[PDB]
Amino acid sequence: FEGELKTLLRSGKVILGTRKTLKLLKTGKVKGVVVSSTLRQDLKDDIMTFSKFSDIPIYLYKGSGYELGTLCGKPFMVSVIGIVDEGESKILEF
RNA sequence: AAGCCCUUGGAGAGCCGUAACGGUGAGAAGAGGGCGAAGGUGUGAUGGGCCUUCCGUUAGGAGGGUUCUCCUGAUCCCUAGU
């Protein structure tokens, strides 16, 4: 799993921050979004509600923003991740 | 004027910011805004109030000015944090 992700950060385009991806996702212009378990529940439904409006695959992450951000490498946590380019990884099928 | 909210915005190997604690990807910075204390300023107030000149000196009568620039300052308030 992590190897697949580590490839995306290497070259594939990524989006960090809910506001941008949530702005973007409603327009149906994202390859995929992965969310850690630590998302505030007020937004989780909206993602799930907006998930079916253009059928964008979503992976649920059991982790928090930290390990997601630790894998992301940013010192601070990331609640969600936005993708507009899979690049060369093999994640989208998930 | 703080605080708290609205868009935009997009930043970390660091940035924002405090008297202090802190805030920051859950959107910081910066731009625009909104709700919005105390107070303050106009008006009320060509009326009185304050001092004062003089003549009248019973009875009263007639004028003058009442500005400007600055400072500290409450245990008297509201406003915030912690």
Image (tube, coloured by chain):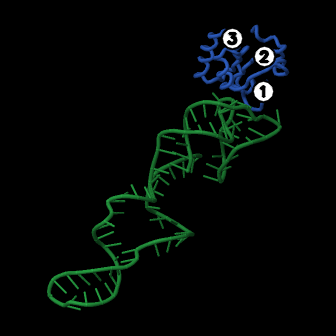
Chain colours: A blue, B green
In the depicted structure, whether residue A29 falls above or below residue B19: above
The mark lying in front, picked from 2 and 1, is 2
Same subunit, labels 2 and 1: the answer reads yes
Residue named by callout 3: A56
- The answer to whether residue B51 is above or below residue B25 is below
x then y, percent, for residue B81: 57, 46
Q: Which residue is mark 1?
A: A70
> Which quadrant is home to the C terminus of chain A?
top right
In the picture, measured across the screen, residue B41 lies left or right of residue A44, that is left
Identify the mark nearer the N-term, 1 or 3.
3
Amino acid found under the numbered disc labelled 2: Asp
State which quarter of the image contains the N terminus of chain A: top right
Q: Earlier in the sequence, mark 2 or mark 3?
A: 3
The residue that mark 2 highlights is A85
Q: Earlier in the sequence, mark 2 or mark 1?
A: 1
Mark 2 crowd level (few <14, some 14–19, many ≥20, 10 Å Cα): some
